[PDB]
Image (cartoon, rainbow over all chains, first blue to last red; front, side):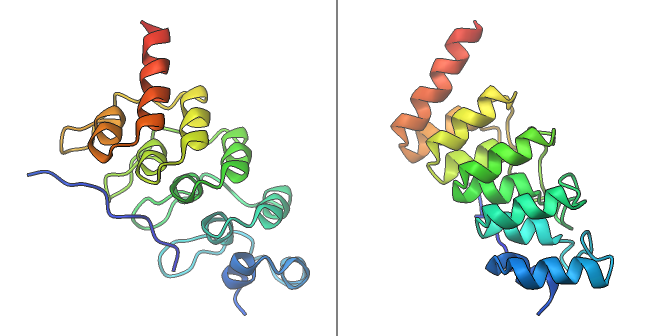
Length: 11
Length: 158
């Protein structure tokens, strides 16, 4: 299953 | 083997056969992925070319708004990125993971892809919901070559 990287997520 | 799988493996014969038998070129799988998206994800240049030449829609998005462009950008498949940019897809579209083609190129340290996106109108100052842009991300990850390309582009605009 083609997947994109989880990108940084800031609170 | 599903048309998606044939595409991902670069099985040109079986894939070309299947497009004859049935109209399935733009058939999506459960996650909304077109064969083209699978081909882009696996850097199958020949297949991407075949699909685009035979009616595959490059603007169709996955369920999470994933694009063939972002998938190819994330892996640094420069030759596929050019082809898809040449289709006239939107360069600045976001998905549900908050990513754009530029942000995935930056994240993967794909300098040539970043250059190509910026030249095609990708805007390095657009921010995620977190408040960071592509320059910010490049600085954060310590990708100095990527940083310089983006800073250089910005400088030429101002």
